[PDB]
Image 1 (cartoon, rainbow over the protein chains, first blue to last red):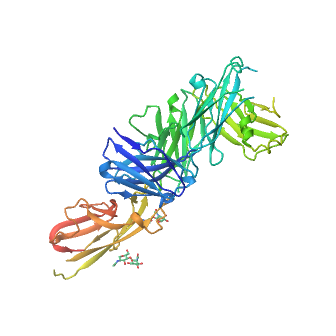
Image 2: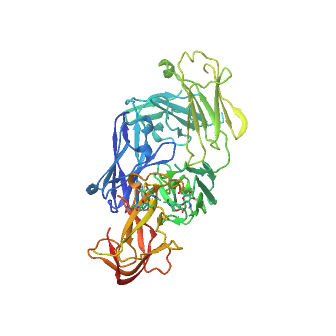
Image 3: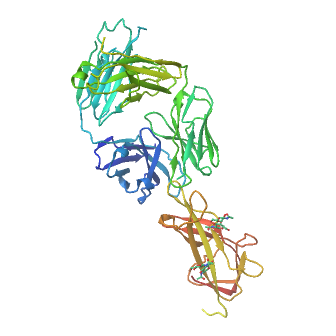
Length: 214
Length: 213
Length: 148
Ligand SMILES: *[C@@H]1O[C@H](CO)[C@@H](O[C@@H]2O[C@H](CO)[C@@H](O)[C@H](O)[C@H]2NC(C)=O)[C@H](O)[C@H]1NC(C)=O
Ligand SMILES: *[C@@H]1O[C@H](CO)[C@@H](O[C@@H]2O[C@H](CO)[C@@H](O)[C@H](O)[C@H]2NC(C)=O)[C@H](O)[C@H]1NC(C)=O
């Protein structure tokens, strides 16, 4: 029952190093190749290199030599990948994936891990700045702007979950060192301005602000 | 460094349709190519192996074809769970490369963007802070195009655009353009039309304002 | 031991190498092997002698998108051609005492051959059969093979 559990999300400063974990189970961890693949947020898959735990035979793509180090604790069933001198371009989600038996040259990668998100950033924990958005057919549409926060994610609701219809929450964008996203809610002029509608922005920076509209 | 090319980048499909995806290698690779699927927020998964070989657990609708430099991924009758990114992988020549990927969207009837513009709020301007936004909610097709301008002509030092992946409800796309500025760069007022253009029609639609009301 | 004549055979096995997408070494089929000429014929070489020794000469070449067998063959991709007991009872290596034949011929063509030798490419990482050395022989006590 093959599965690969990867380590949690990392959030690291530039010039520092990281080491990702990948514990395998359901098959013989020592007899199958373990590949590592880099996926960048907008883009495709970049093969990093493989390692055969049976000894520790270690390959690498030219692009990744010196940056990625692969190890495997045989009796631990866990496979690791160490990255050095992290940079903005190193930010991404890294998959660990299963391959063929020793002398297989052309295998497809069998089972993959849930992925590990690695963000490289110089930025410090900053709390979000929220602002109200105001201006029929008649569905009135109103936003709620959050700006200047870090890290992600931010979680946004409306009227405390008692409203889920014309709501969108645009993917966060990097504007600066910091993020900015907007929400959109649409309703009938009947209820608003007539009844209170407050957006709810939360930030695991153990922080939270609620805004109304006028 | 053999380059794989998938065409087209994006493919509109409806449930039940027949579909074919494409992958062309720089050079011959025999049948040493694999196909992977990756649903949103998900992890890649092998659909077809050695481009024709079927994989245990994969539904009958997936099949592979090709040998040499041309390859194709086939989906007999498209299902809703089939919306995803598809990547071909070359495993013949070192090192093993992937294609840019082909993304599947859901096809629906066209629709126009509800544009809603917004003035800076009273806290923003306090913080010497400012910024002006524009929603273009619930439209299609995705392929759209925006224009800010101030007392007429173009302005485009820093606008940030964010996009919304297809809606799992109405199957439409929404977009936010935000235009962040200082206040004196803003006390320099004149006019803030966020025009919009879209296949939908040659209405550049505008919504605008001067200083408030 | 003693001989009246001792022909020594120099076999050249030029093995070509490629590597797969995951950096796996792959010995190209039709790495070339060449036998000494002999008569209005080269393809096969019978040993007209009461004793003989064999000398393998290996050469490796790398390859990419092409089969342009131009390049060194360094890192794992290296190679040393090895000759292996294919389908015939004798090894072609040192098992103490000596091979004995009344006849012994190496053919590049599988015609009328008694058995094969599996010419392969040894590397740190794995070993891979590339071509076949066909060998026509007759059990006897006239010809004697020495190492190697
Ligand atoms: C066996 O024959 C091969 C040719 O099949 C000889 O190859 C030569 O290798 C030397 C270096 O060892 C080079 O200088 C020559 O240029 C090669 N010649 C050719 C024609 O390839 C090899 O010398 C022979 N080995 C012995 C010891 O007889
Ligand atoms: C084995 O022999 C053939 C020649 O008889 C070689 O194949 C040629 O190789 C060169 C490049 O290496 C090409 O220019 C020719 O077009 C090839 N000819 C044929 C018939 O394919 C081959 O390279 C040799 N193998 C090795 C390992 O050198």
